[PDB]
Length: 164
Ligand SMILES: [Ca+2]
Ligand SMILES: [Ca+2]
Ligand SMILES: [Ca+2]
Ligand SMILES: [Zn+2]
Ligand SMILES: [Zn+2]
Image 1 (cartoon, rainbow, N blue to C red):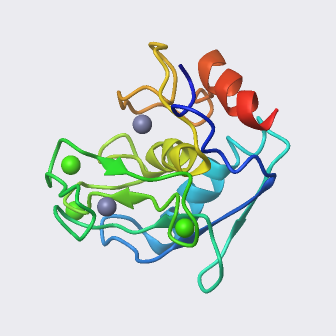
Image 2: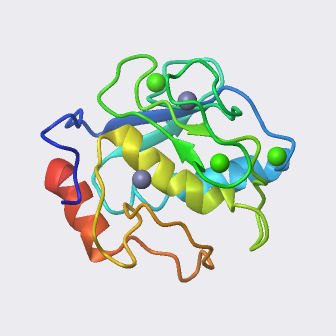
């Protein structure tokens, strides 16, 4: 079931992301480093196109917030809900939100922003959840070297099932 319940996906090859705010847990460089790589893992598995912006119209709006921040979701700070984003949304759709309470970093320590970023955008695109024990869509999170980190068959199968 590597895909949202239906067909919320925009079904377009034009996407973008805009980081509303930056967390003190990551570095100005690490933020763009982990992100650029995140989108480079999905834009390579689909004939789509992703772009970065700080003052434009992006699909995946990244906003690091803590607990309840006006999203009817109310995070859980340290541990728990690492992050949550949308998909079939306009202007503010696919808005990815990361729990600031968490320790986002570029190493195996804190919650690697890179990995979390990749899967974060997936939801903003309109992807669902996979049952693969190694699928990014999986609700489970785990650190992994970017050199070894790759979208599982389920992820690539789903992402392409709506874009391919
Ligand atoms: Ca959390
Ligand atoms: Ca948006
Ligand atoms: Ca923090
Ligand atoms: Zn939120
Ligand atoms: Zn997920």
